[PDB]
Length: 76
Image (cartoon, rainbow, N blue to C red; front, side, top):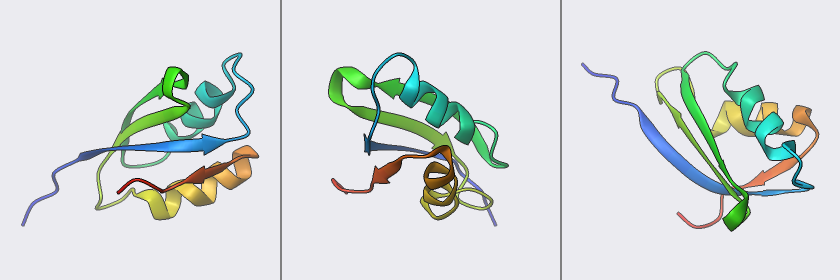
């Protein structure tokens, strides 16, 4: 009936500051069903908003790997 989008917030591995994680997530800003990407290296974390119809963690890991890093869906 609906498609209501959500924020995920999760930790990344391999970021060496200097817009690295920004590049990672900006990669995800290209994925069909993302809306926005917001890096939080002050907490070694990144937040990304997407629609679970087209986009989720599933596709996201896939691309993150190709960006040349691995994200950790630890937390919740």
